[PDB]
Image (tube, rainbow over all chains, first blue to last red):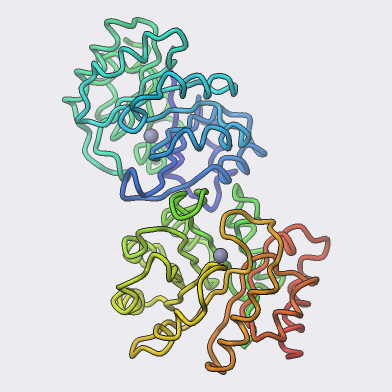
Length: 219
Length: 219
Ligand SMILES: [Zn+2]
Ligand SMILES: [Zn+2]
């Protein structure tokens, strides 16, 4: 199924409640929340508290991308906060993915995993195949850090690879996605698109979302 | 001079723009922003991005309290974001306070320093006396982590001590400040008060602010 989740990171943070409600109105399936602690990536954005306050205003799906080092330590707070999706990083999740995916799941959150550009795609299959597996895989399409970097087409090799072995797994692409790049990723197998400036900086935001969706469905 | 800065951390994060504008209306002199990376304290709140979006909505003074480990790395972003005051922690700022205070200053922000409960007050005098010194000292009145902890009167010893040697230095108290405790701190020497639940959870928020101020001036 197609899923177009705007990256609230490129929105008016002073007006999350507003922005969030406006994206659904325009077609937002999910709301992509990037939580960074400045240690895993040279940048600190938002944490649990935020997520929580936002849940008191919208019932939308909150896709939480955990770019932190101590993810296990966020599972409890984010759950309470009301996160819908919890996605961790294979890099720091080495050696507990099995326990982690279970903690996440047992909290009512859809567990997911992600891998930076330079991380062999193979590394997730084990996590995608486990008894209690992740239900989504996020493929970083740029070096994780700040919004506005150049889309990396090479990363598409990972999308196709995934899509082949797993025909119905939600595959998410995050970084640079927009009209100009949606197609190359749509054909690769991505069905969960995260858009940032391509939406919050468009004259026709609603339109843009409607275009990312078609792309994916026309695939 | 008295300064009553509400702690935006206890506000409706989904509506910062709103909340912030509402506090000025009621009397807020400054807006206390607590930036935590989860590594210096088991909690992650908000980072530069937020601060920035918020600057596009208000001209209020943004008092930034940096509870991070790598503070020097936030000086550049916060400056651009529009922070008015940059306050770092003596614990992690050991060995560069001189260079740090200068970086902060040279960016147009008022440099400040803070010390957890268990940190000998003496440790800041050097920083308060330097050629390019800090212009404010924050005295943690509770163990740094989450809003809602018990005020620690003992910590007042530090306020008095500071106020004595430095008669006109802005002294800030953060943690549990409210009507019930403003006086003990007002008499000690504190003139910059940071209030959280005592304001955002009051029936007469505006009134509360007016009460914290009198306390201080009646001193
Ligand atoms: Zn993301
Ligand atoms: Zn503070």
